[PDB]
Image 1 (tube, helix red, strand yellow):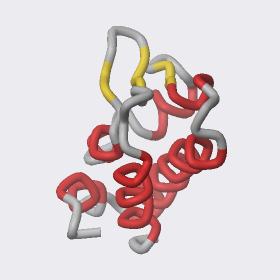
Image 2 (image 1 turned 30 degrees about the horizontal axis):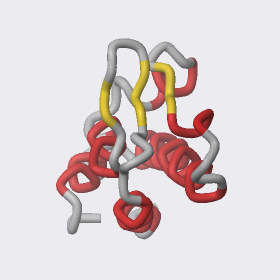
Image 3 (image 1 turned 180 degrees about the vertical axis):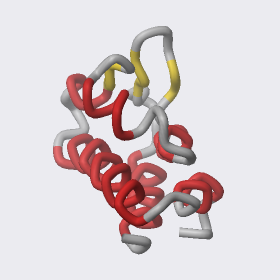
Image 4 (image 1 turned 90 degrees about the vertical axis):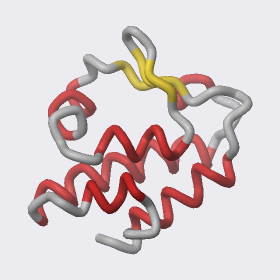
Length: 99
């Protein structure tokens, strides 16, 4: 939680919103951790229903993805092939312990 600036920001949300955003964040991280060699899990379309309605408008949500290693592009958030999976897991854990 507080050990992460983005998670600390995410914590500044009501319970239901925090749980909803954090669940999706954990799903994105877990998909990559489950299959780190599948490019499908390394791209999140900004216009995606879940992303646009549960993360984009929530304080700290997208920032957590950036701390995980995602980078923002014109239409997608991308987790580079060079991005550290250890860092991804670190932020994943910091989010999980706050649910």
